[PDB]
Amino acid sequence: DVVVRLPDVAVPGEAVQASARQAVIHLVDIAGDYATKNLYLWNNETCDALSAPVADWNDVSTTPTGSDKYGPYWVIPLTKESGCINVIVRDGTNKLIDSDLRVSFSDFTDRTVSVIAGNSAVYDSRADAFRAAFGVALADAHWVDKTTLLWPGGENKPIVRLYYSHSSKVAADSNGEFSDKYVKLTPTTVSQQVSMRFPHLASYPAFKLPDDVNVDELLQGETVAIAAESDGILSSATQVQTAGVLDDTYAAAAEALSYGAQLTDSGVTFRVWAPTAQQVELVIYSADKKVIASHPMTRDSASGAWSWQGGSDLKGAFYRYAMTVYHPQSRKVEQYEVTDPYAHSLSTNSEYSQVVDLNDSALKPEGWDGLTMPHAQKTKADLAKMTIHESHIRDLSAWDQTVPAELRGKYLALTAQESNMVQHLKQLSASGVTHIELLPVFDLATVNEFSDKVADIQQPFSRLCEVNSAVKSSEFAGYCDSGSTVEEVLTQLKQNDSKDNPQVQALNTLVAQTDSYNWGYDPFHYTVPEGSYATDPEGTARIKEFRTMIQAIKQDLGMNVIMDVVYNHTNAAGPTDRTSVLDKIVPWYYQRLNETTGSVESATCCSDSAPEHRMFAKLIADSLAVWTTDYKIDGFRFDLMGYHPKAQILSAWERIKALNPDIYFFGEGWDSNQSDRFEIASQINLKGTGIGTFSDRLRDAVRGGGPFDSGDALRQNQGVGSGAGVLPNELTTLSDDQARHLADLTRLGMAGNLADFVLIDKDGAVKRGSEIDYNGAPGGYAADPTEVVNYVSKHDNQTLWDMISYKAAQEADLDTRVRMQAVSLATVMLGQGIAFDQQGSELLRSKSFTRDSYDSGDWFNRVDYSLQDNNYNVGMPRSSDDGSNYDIIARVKDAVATPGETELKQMTAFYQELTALRKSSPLFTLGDGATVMKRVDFRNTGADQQTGLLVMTIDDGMQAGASLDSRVDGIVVAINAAPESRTLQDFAGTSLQLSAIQQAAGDRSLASGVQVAADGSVTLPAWSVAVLELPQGESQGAGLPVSSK
Ligand SMILES: [Mg+2]
Ligand SMILES: [Mg+2]
Ligand SMILES: [Mg+2]
Ligand SMILES: [Mg+2]
Ligand SMILES: [Mg+2]
Ligand SMILES: [Mg+2]
Ligand SMILES: [Mg+2]
Ligand SMILES: [Mg+2]
Ligand SMILES: [Mg+2]
Ligand SMILES: [Mg+2]
Ligand SMILES: [Mg+2]
Ligand SMILES: [Mg+2]
């Protein structure tokens, strides 16, 4: 075999070295035209060392100072020799490096650097750039099955090889020869199996390893793909992504096993999947975290799993896995201890995993095993009744002075039957809220569970300074030795807070670093409860407390429980970070990587996971199985579900239905951009599967605008619920046509956002739901309404009240704005889709305009169950994300008074009326899409409609089929989202009756002032909601037949 070696050419010296007040940049012409090469140079805040850089982007005259055969270079004048400079390397006005370069004079003290076109790295010399160009670079080779490598670098090259080194890096030796062992590769054609697994790589050149290759040998260390010419000079070399071959080699054998510290009465078996590790030891720790044993584990050859079996005396023991494993990011054989990705119990702050048997009676509240789901979820009609209250453990109880102090912010607050919060939830349940959805209660990373390291706003400012050095070094340091609590300081800061002095958020942003508050979309361990919500985060105690909460919700409050789950990302990856678990144990397998660099992708926010890989799909299903069986969770909401393959979500659902036949799955099925890799679990792709998705259609039509809005657009973009068209504010330009389009989306959503539902649009045209456009997408997408989750408020983005406050006309008074809140919620609560709402919408909840409140603390997330106010106007929201909105906030904020007890009680009554109406007839919750189509229609449609009046009919008459409600032959839902009184004339001669529920509320009803006249006409006041019924006589009547279209 020919030996592969570096180019036998001289390594380039420097063309020139920077002198005083100069920088030098070489463009190293690695590719075997210099006059058109030029630099764009500019000073900004962070880099400002350039002397008089040319201002005009179009000026291409900063051409090379000199050049030679190794390329051109530039000498650049500076005003100082410290700091950095901004550089874009161009040909003409086109970038030759896609990255905007930053040349650091601290990383390159001689200020003489080198770059290569198409390469974002900055080198200290042309020699370094040259050796990098002919060395291991990037990671664009993919070893996808036993014998197949996909690699663009190997195309049309005679020598293509897979070099490998068990304990070091593949590199050229002192002679310049690559002397590590290798396997010869040959051109081949990709198999269909591989093409279906990796469609985004299917067009890459394919190469074949010998059928007798010892894969386990190569996978234990570094592998590098190397291409060369016939003479044997290296052409390119790159690192190898191995997840595909790991699945092809090990996944079936590994899928057949179970993982974690599996404790039963006979003993314990520990198992961890680590098919590339060179060694795995099980380290057992005492309660005081001293090592008491380190056990070499036993590797199984078929699966690449490691196991160790011991006695039941290991119950309660702490443990970690000591890994010896090559990590391709660092290119080192790393040595570190890692917690179990299958941990079911943890020490404080997740430092050690703990052996537990979740079946143990000591970890269960009394009567746990007999806990039943209070609301059915079997049929589609059952599911359609789902009415969700999306809640957070701290948002519930952090402020409730009637919850015992030691339970504030804890799972166990739900057991405080004497508290305002629990009594309020109990009344919401009695009125028709059916499900609590919990924000992250698995083990999150972003709260410190060591209570000594945390300071909350109810505690002395002196404590804050002790735990938070940023506060102690800030402009607020003078409060350190005050006798005030943090919340007392924040309160005194309100009066002088404004857009010109956002001092409340200035202090609160520092507080956020060390408080107990986070939404928790930051997974540390997927299958252990979060510790900070327990009264004792050390060891197994949180398990029973979590179960006590679940039992309280289901048995005592009468609501089902949904968990938010976050399998689309990990909190961290790589070999170093505290919270990198999976990516330490099987590096490069559990994360989705860029096809060229091997970098962990971050489209989700964080460290994107790879649910398309078999062992991560298994981890997800196994995790859901524990939450289902051991924690009696009734449904799951998948965060960023579009990052998951449709096939993976469906397989998980099949697996969980074997454990709980009525489990319900839904998620955020927004487009994830992953369709090139697999069919994504999106709104459209899930049609007909029974997996629900949040609908953005009715949401945005009723709220107005969308999550990206900033500045004046927040006010201009009124929604149906805030008077689009009919009650314009001073900035909007919405036309009547635009407002009527939003009403088309709203009606479609009230009918379950079905693709095939037939309506009359704003122009009088007959349209299917899929033909009503939503921001350039088919609006209706579902097969059944139980596939659609409607909402107008959620933890993310502004609260409904804050949206109404941005959008409402100046003349809309406070009482009108409360009715706008209720009218907005009526479109959800009286619609056929599953109903979902944010905790506190019934209390006009505000976040003081905060759009994204995940780390905005108790202050901005406060819900006041004592009913004094709605948390509006408590300071400008965080400047980093809402500073662009300070101008519009200042202009709208004080239009009307802040809600107090009167408005909060009024809104709670409106809310409970809506949820009671939703459950008052099976007709609101038909479940089956074909049944919706046969029974649901709309009036007041087309070009002659009265804008803002939504009139929905639901048929129970003979033309619909059977009577599903023995009391009525039909229902009319009329939502008059407008400042005028409206009269309905199309039910003349039929004698409708107002719902008994609305009658019983009298002048506190949303239908207060509705008139049903002798001629059958119905008059609705401004901003009202009426549910009217056709009473059923001795036999089923004519009803309200759907009109043929
Ligand atoms: Mg310029
Ligand atoms: Mg240098
Ligand atoms: Mg080929
Ligand atoms: Mg007990
Ligand atoms: Mg935690
Ligand atoms: Mg103020
Ligand atoms: Mg925080
Ligand atoms: Mg405590
Ligand atoms: Mg991609
Ligand atoms: Mg589109
Ligand atoms: Mg409140
Ligand atoms: Mg009937």
Image (cartoon, grey):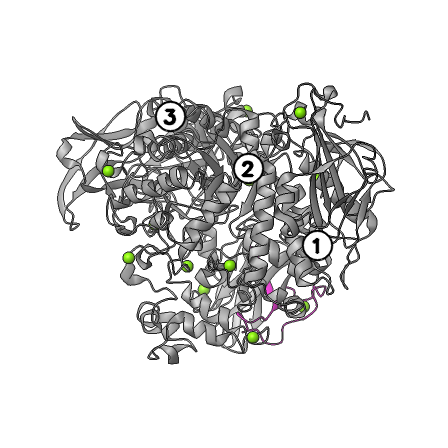
Callout 2–callout 3 Cβ contact below 8 Å: no
Judge left or right: residue 1011 versus residue 261.
Answer: right
Residue 724 pos. (x, y %): 75, 53
Three-letter residue code for mark 1? Ser
| Whole-number angstrom distance, CA of label 2 to CA of label 1 | 31 Å
Ligand 10: which quarter? top right
Ligand 9 has an atom within 8 Å of the beta carbon of the residue at disc 3: no
| Residue hosting label 3 | 251
Three-letter residue code for mark 3? Ala
At a point 76% along the width and 25% down the height, the residue shown is 1041
- Magenta-tinted stretch: 41-69
Q: Main secondary structure of the magenta part?
A: loop
| Whole-number angstrom distance, CA of label 1 to CA of label 3 | 54 Å
Residue 578 pos. (x, y %): 33, 51
Point out the image quarter for the N terminus: top left
Residue 147 pos. (x, y %): 43, 23
Helix, strand or loop at disc 2? Answer: helix
Callout 2–callout 1 Cβ contact below 8 Å: no
Three-letter residue code for mark 2? Gly
Q: Is residue 62 magenta?
A: yes
Judge left or right: residue 161 versus residue 915.
Answer: left
> Is residue 521 depicted above or below 485 in this figure?
above
| Whole-number angstrom distance, CA of label 2 to CA of label 3 | 24 Å
Q: Nearer the viewer, residue 231 or 999?
A: 999
> Is residue 1045 depicted above or below 152 in this figure?
above
Query: Disc 2 or 3, which lies upstream in sequence?
Result: 3
> Is residue 346 depicted above or below 41 in this figure?
above
Query: Disc 1 or 3, which lies upstream in sequence?
Result: 3
| Mark carried by residue 722 | 1
Q: Is residue 354 magenta?
A: no
| Mark carried by residue 642 | 2
Residue 884 in view (yes/no): yes
